[PDB]
Amino acid sequence: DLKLVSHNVYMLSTVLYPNWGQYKRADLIGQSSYIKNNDVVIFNEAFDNGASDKLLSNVKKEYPYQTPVLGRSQSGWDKTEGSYSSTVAEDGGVAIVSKYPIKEKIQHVFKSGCGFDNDSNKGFVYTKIEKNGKNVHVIGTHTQSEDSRCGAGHDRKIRAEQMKEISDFVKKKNIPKDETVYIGGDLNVNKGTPEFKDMLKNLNVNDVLYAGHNSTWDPQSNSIAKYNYPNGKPEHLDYIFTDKDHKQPKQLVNEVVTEKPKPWDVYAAAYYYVYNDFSDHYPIKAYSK
Ligand SMILES: [Ca+2]
Ligand SMILES: [Ca+2]
Ligand SMILES: [Cl-]
Ligand SMILES: [Cl-]
C-alpha cells in the first residue's frame, strides 16, 4: 500500500511578499525527515515559481517523476480540464512528485469559485502511477479557504461544489474498482463540524484513523500561523483519503507531523523576526498500518 505525504507549504509570491523566507524553507523541507521514505508527495501553495522549482529540485533525487505546478501553463500535461485561464497572475500551487513513474497526468481548474477575492487557478492534479506492476491513482488538491473575502456561507458552498467536481471526475474517468484512488490536500474543512460529514459525501470517501497532532493549522504551536492570526482557532484541514468506491487500503491513517526545522530568521523594514516551522500548515503522512 502507498505511503504519502501531503503539505501546504506557504510559498507565497516573493514579489508581493519578499521576506517570508521562501527559498530557505524550500531547502529546509528538502532536508526534513518527513519528506523522506514516502512513495508520493502532494504540495499545495507552491505559488512562487522560483522557490517552487527549487523545492522540486530538492526532492528530484528521491522523487524523480514530477508533474508541473497546477495552472502555470498548458505544457507538460496529458490534458487540461475546467476553467483554465492563461491571463491570471498566480497559478494553482498544486504539484505531485512520485518515487515511481507517472503514466498519466492531468490538471483541472475548478469551474466553481469566487469572482472577486482572487484570480487563481485552484483545482486538482490527477496522476496514474505504476507500482509493482499494478496501477494506483493519486489526486492532489487545494479547495476554497475560509480566508474568503466572499459572502457568509459561500466558501462552504464553493468547496462543496469544488469537491463534487473531483468525485465526478473520478466517476467518469472510470477507474478499475480494484485500483485505489487517493484524494488528498488542504481541503479547508474543519474536523468535527457538520461540514466534515458533507466533505465525506461530496468527495465520496470514508473517514480515516488519525495519529499525532490534533490540528494541521495551529496558531498555538506553529510560529508562522501564530504571527498571521495570534488569536485564531486551531483547525484540522489537511487530509489524505481514498475513493470509497475503489480499493480500500488496509487501514488508512493520517499522521499529523510536527517536525520543526532549526530556526530561520529575516529582516523586514526596521524589524527582525525568528521562526521555526516549514509552513503555517503541518505536513501529514498517510499509510496503511
Ligand atoms: Ca494558506
Ligand atoms: Ca488555507
Ligand atoms: Cl514581506
Ligand atoms: Cl514577516
Image: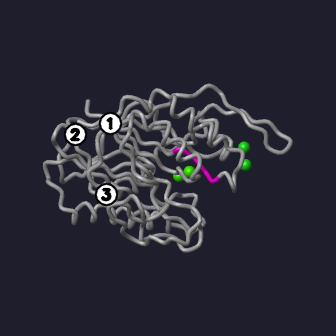
State the SS at label 3. helix
Residue 131 is tagged as 2
Residue 146 position within the rendered picture, expressed as x and y whole percent measured from the top left: 54, 58
Mark 3 nearby-residue class (10 Å; few <14, some 14–19, many ≥20): many
Q: CA distance from mark 1 to mark 2?
A: 9 Å
Tell me which corner region of the image, top left, top right, bottom left or bottom right, holds residue 284: top left
**Residues shaded magenta:** 9-13
Q: Identify the residue under disc 3.
A: 203
113, 124: nearer the viewer: 124
Residue 39 is tagged as 1
Q: Is 52 covered by the magenta stretch?
A: no
Residue at image position (33%, 37%) is: 99
187, 261: nearer the viewer: 261
The amino acid type, in three-letter code, at marker 3 is: Leu
Residue at image position (36%, 37%) is: 254
Q: Main secondary structure of the magenta part?
A: strand
The amino acid type, in three-letter code, at marker 1 is: Asp
